[PDB]
Amino acid sequence: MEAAHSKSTEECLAYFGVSETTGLTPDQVKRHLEKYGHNELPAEEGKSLWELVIEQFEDLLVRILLLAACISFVLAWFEEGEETITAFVEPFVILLILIANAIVGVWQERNAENAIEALKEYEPEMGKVYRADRKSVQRIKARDIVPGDIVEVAVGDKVPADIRILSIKSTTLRVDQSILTGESVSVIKHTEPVPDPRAVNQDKKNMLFSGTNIAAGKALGIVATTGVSTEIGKIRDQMAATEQDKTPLQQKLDEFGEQLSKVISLICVAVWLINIGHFNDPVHGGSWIRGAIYYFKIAVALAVAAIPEGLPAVITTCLALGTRRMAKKNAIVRSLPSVETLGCTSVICSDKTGTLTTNQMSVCKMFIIDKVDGDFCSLNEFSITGSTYAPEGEVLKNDKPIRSGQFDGLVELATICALCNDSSLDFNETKGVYEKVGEATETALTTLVEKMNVFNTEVRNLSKVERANACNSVIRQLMKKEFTLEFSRDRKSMSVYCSPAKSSRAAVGNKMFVKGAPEGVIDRCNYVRVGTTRVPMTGPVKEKILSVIKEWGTGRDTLRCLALATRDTPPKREEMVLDDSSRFMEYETDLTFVGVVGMLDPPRKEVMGSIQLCRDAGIRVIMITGDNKGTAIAICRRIGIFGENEEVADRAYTGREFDDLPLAEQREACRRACCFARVEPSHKSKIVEYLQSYDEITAMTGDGVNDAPALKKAEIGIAMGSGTAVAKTASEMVLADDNFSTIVAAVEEGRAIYNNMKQFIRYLISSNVGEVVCIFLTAALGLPEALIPVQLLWVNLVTDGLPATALGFNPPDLDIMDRPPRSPKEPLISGWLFFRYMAIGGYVGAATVGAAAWWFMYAEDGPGVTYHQLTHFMQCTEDHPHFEGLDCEIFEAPEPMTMALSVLVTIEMCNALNSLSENQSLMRMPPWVNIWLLGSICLSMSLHFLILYVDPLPMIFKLKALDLTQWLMVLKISLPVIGLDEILKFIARNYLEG
Ligand SMILES: [Ca+2]
Ligand SMILES: [Ca+2]
Ligand SMILES: [Ca+2]
Ligand SMILES: [Ca+2]
Ligand SMILES: [Cl-]
Ligand SMILES: [K+]
């Protein structure tokens, strides 16, 4: 809908056939969506490259390798047996392979950039729009907005796309389009056209350019364009290409792609030397330089086979797929390069309120009397679940569920909780969460009655707005609150005067429900309600009550307690003066203690266990807060930062105590601290500084400009999703819920996104080192060659390239949080890991130069046989010493090389199955965990059988199809790799790390 600035509002509403009263419709959305794409700008420009030097090392090798195959046959294309066809088509083979190496190398290149696209649902404009389905506004993602739908914007909003204003709801509408125009002041917009189709944006006084924000006003409009069709979109697309610095894992990995290339470049250039003894020999046209181009091919080939390809792309996938994974968990990563650091987090600094704690008061404990006949009374203690103002949760006794209604004592406790209250619950259908109305401590009660629901009302069926104050209303339908006696610090309590509702009488049923702080309320109780009874307040009982009120108010939970009682025979309203707190303490006498409830601000979901997790992963959790030292210290023993009876007289500090210490004592405080209370805004940054001094990677939560500095200085800034825009742009990550338990998970995924890479690296390296050992172990202990040029190319393609990319789809490893956080100090590969590599690779290479050895040497019923004097085979000429029913041309036999190459491939897939997780079992994580692997394995295992059995080919590959016994061998020869590595894993899993 270009040039919408020159068209009537009608011409546009028409062009989209949308009614501005109800905006678009589902199918219109999907329709326009497909025709114009999502409201985003792509990455069509170059902003990424193949970090490794070797990727450009190999591509030159496969080019020059081909050259050798064009000089090879050419120099002398005529042999005694003209052209065997298995040395004539080689040029046609390698090239047929480089093509496969390509089709594959670009297969993984896509997934790598296909996953990037998966992460395009981050922190967008969230523009507002009107669609058919609903009548009220719709806060939808900026990208989900299609040209054509109806968008409205009020003060402060950011313009999500190019909008042709339709209606201006405010007396006027100024906008700030400073970012796109030479206009510093906000300008006005109007609802009419601007005929001239080629006028400049400054003169498009009726449009709202995307990426702009309105200074003042509200106004509806219709999206002309979106995406790159946007005025700001035609700009950013046409911008200067951006460059970047590099991360310590990239550096350490580039240093790695420098070690290998070199070594490789010598493991092979050492082959064109260990095989000098065969350059002249017959098999190679019986000339020198001709063999000097055959062993060249092998080396330049062995290289290609060893060069672990795919790393850059694969990482980018784990990375991508992982971030996707984090987001599902509310961890919106803003900087990919940072997720790298994320697993090196060694200290998290979090704020208490909202993040570690819910900040919604919740009753979690309550009791009442059970028995008292024997001058020794027991009680009925109940626990309550659910830690917010939402009606969700259930009453428990001895960790077991019970109906609140079955206990008559509770029915009154609720009646009090229900009536002696001035607060309520409200469902904010907008935010889809339960809100409180008034004081929290009261509201906490409200929610208790709901979780109680002593009268088994039907709730499930009700609407959220309905479940809000359900059970609470029932009680109000049975008891009329006449008047209330306001609070007062003299008696520290309050109460109400109630009487049966609808009851058309007086002086009957009247009761006064009193609620207050324990002591005082208990001392005004002369009677104590048991069952439905009421026995006088003896000396022993009153002791029992106060005893638990202590066990509760002091214990690890440190619950705030409230005493619930009723005045059975209240004075009459007449004889009562309600205009001074002075007399109220009096009317509130001769009470019958009903029960007590204990509330507290509960720790957010999982936070209690997440802290335990950090603990297992050596991460320091430091709580920053506004509380007082004492209460703050408490909250820490409540959540776990501190054991219930752990001495922490030096790991909690308050702003002032801290400023009072000397720099050297401040730095020390931080290497041990775990709680900070009443902190000046400038302490966070100071705290981090001291944290950095002990080389500690630190994640700091913030939520206001107040934290901007601290957020930036930290290794990882983490902004509250409920925070300010400033803090969000200062952090490298955002908490959608503002929950602490997230950070811990984000951190964990970091550990997996690393471990994934390590699975990928280990599989190539361990496997390829195994190839290089076969080519070597034959040329070593002297043996009939096991592989030739095109076979190396084959193996490469079948075990690098595809089942390799697969692993990038491996899932999150386990017991990944019991190690200390990674330090950018320690090396890419640990000495034991390298062993673990050679342990494997050294084996595979054996199994291969031990599969053909089984073909040549004895074999249950083998088609050929000889003895370990096979190491001298080349001197065979029927010399009459080691001769039998054998001919010197049996050392050219195809099946051996085929019993080999087939062992290689199958052994590697058996190995790729080991790359599902660094130190776990195939038992604890089956091969089917990652499907794409099983797939890629088969898709390759197949390309192998196809080369062996499809007659026009096994000839080119100098191979010769093996039978069911010849394949049952390959299995028992390669399958035992699982067995081995499964041991190394076992070891490490218990002996090494601990
Ligand atoms: Ca008009
Ligand atoms: Ca390779
Ligand atoms: Ca440092
Ligand atoms: Ca391989
Ligand atoms: Cl108009
Ligand atoms: K930073």
Image: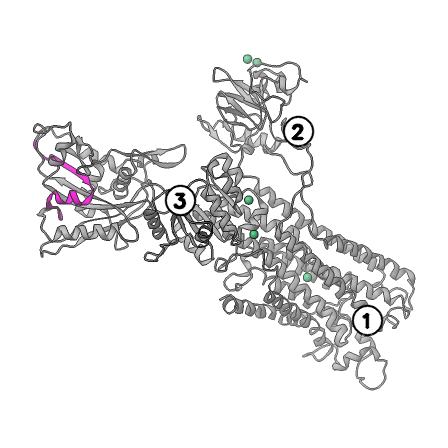
Amino acid, disc 1: Asn
* Relative depth, front residue between 670 and 656: 656
Residue range highlighted in magenta: 507-532
Q: Quadrant of ligand 4?
A: bottom right
Q: Nearer the viewer, mark 3 or mark 2?
A: 3
User: Is residue 908 depicted above or below 311 in this figure?
Assistant: below
Lower position in the chain sequence, tag 3 or tag 2: 2
Per the image, the residue denoted by label 1 is: 275
Amino acid, disc 2: Lys
Per the image, the residue denoted by label 3 is: 655
Label 3 C-beta lies within 8 Å of the nearest ligand 6 atom: no
The residue tagged with tag 2: helix, strand or loop? helix
Which residue is painted at 25% across and 49% down in the image? Answer: 553
Is residue 950 in view? no
The residue tagged with tag 3: helix, strand or loop? helix
**Image-quadrant location for residue 300:** bottom right
* Relative depth, front residue between 98 and 634: 634
User: Is residue 90 depicted above or below 879 in this figure?
Assistant: above
Q: Nearer the viewer, mark 1 or mark 3?
A: 3
Give the Cα separation between the discs numbered 3 and 2: 51 Å
The disc placed on residue 234 is: 2
Lower position in the chain sequence, tag 2 or tag 1: 2
Residue 506 image point, x, y percent: 8, 29
Quadrant of the image containing the N terminus: top right
The residue tagged with tag 1: helix, strand or loop? loop
Q: Residue furthest front?
A: 662
* Relative depth, front residue between 917 and 751: 751
The 10 Å Cα crowd at callout 1, few under 14, some 14 to 19, many 20 or more, is some
Is residue 309 in view? yes
- 243 relative to 813 in the view: left or right: right
- 15 relative to 778 in the view: left or right: left
Amino acid, disc 3: Gly
